[PDB]
Structure formats: structure tokens, C-alpha cells
Amino acid sequence: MRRVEKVIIVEGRSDKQKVAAVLNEPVVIVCTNGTISDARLEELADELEGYDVYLLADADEAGEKLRRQFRRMFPEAEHLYIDRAYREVAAAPIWHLAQVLLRARFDVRIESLM
């Protein structure tokens, strides 16, 4: 078993469970549980030095706020986007989330495309 390097950060509990369900490799999924303080974000950035980190936020206002915080506090994190036509990670079809992750080079379950 090789070391786990990938990390996806999401805002919401259901986002986390939904992401975890599509993945076919071990990935640390961090949920901010809504807003996260600058200090907790800095700590996370420190802890995650050398990791391959992604932020997947809703295409809405709250999501954009979190992205803005990340651009300031945690520039290392790569931003992933659902089609803003689905708006929320929670709303997006399983296959769409799977394709977003696959485009970013995550292993996803084939079943998540059916």
C-alpha cells in the first residue's frame, strides 16, 4: 500500500460522503463544516505541505467565499469546479462529480458512471 497523497476539501458533510462514494482510491477528505477560521486553515496548509490538495466548493456565494479565503490562506490548494449549471456539489449527478474528479486524475468507481 503506497502512501496517501491526495486530499479533497469540501464545505459540507453530505459533500464529503458523496465524494467518498465515487472514489476508487484512498483520499483524505476534509470537511470544513461550513466556515473555517484563518488559523485552522493555516494549520491545515502547514499539515498538508507536500500533499496533493484540491478544493471542491459549490458554485454559489458561500462556495465563492470559501474559495476566496483559500486563495489568500492556502494558495497551494487546486480549485475543482462542478458545472455552475448544477450549482451545488450536493445537487450534481453522481456521474458528473465522478467526471470532475476523473478529469483531475482521481480513480473513480465505474459504477459511479452508471
Image (cartoon, rainbow, N blue to C red):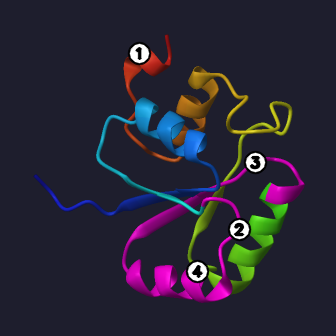
Q: Please report whichever mark, 2 or 4, sits nearer to the chain's N-terminal start.
A: 2
Q: Please report whichever mark, 3 or 4, sits nearer to the chain's N-terminal start.
A: 4
Mark 1 — residue? 111
2 or 4: mark nearer the eye: 2
Residue situated furthest left in the rendering: 1
Percent position of residue 18, x then y: 52, 34
Q: Please report whichever mark, 2 or 3, sits nearer to the chain's N-terminal start.
A: 2
Question: Label 4: few (<14), some or many (≥20) within 10 Å?
Answer: some
Mark 3 — residue? 58
- Does the magenta portion include 112? no
Secondary structure at badge 2 equals loop
- Inter-mark Cα distance, 1 to 3: 24 Å
Residue contact at pointers 3 and 4, CB within 8 angstroms: no
Q: Please report whichever mark, 1 or 4, sits nearer to the chain's N-terminal start.
A: 4
Q: Please report whichever mark, 2 or 1, sits nearer to the chain's N-terminal start.
A: 2
Of the residues shown, which amino acid type is indicated by label 2? Thr
Mark 4 — residue? 41
Q: Please report whichever mark, 1 or 3, sits nearer to the chain's N-terminal start.
A: 3
Of the residues shown, which amino acid type is indicated by label 1? Glu
Q: Residue at x 75, y 76 (%)?
A: 69
Of the residues shown, which amino acid type is indicated by label 4? Leu
Mark 2 — residue? 35
